[PDB]
Length: 44
Ligand SMILES: [Zn+2]
Figure 1 (cartoon, helix red, strand yellow):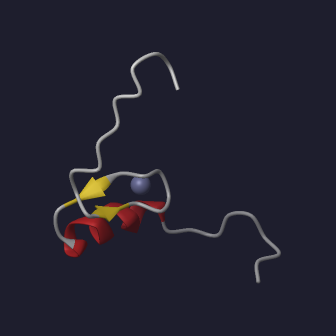
Figure 2 (cartoon, helix red, strand yellow):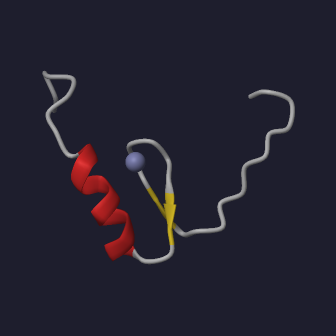
């Protein structure tokens, strides 16, 4: 956390992948479309 810690969660919807933000779910999903994938096998 470089000097500054400039982080404000203005948007409710956040990307569980990177942490992005969005005003409406529909908006977030669109950004998740690319994230979608099969990483880290052996999931439960
Ligand atoms: Zn993301």
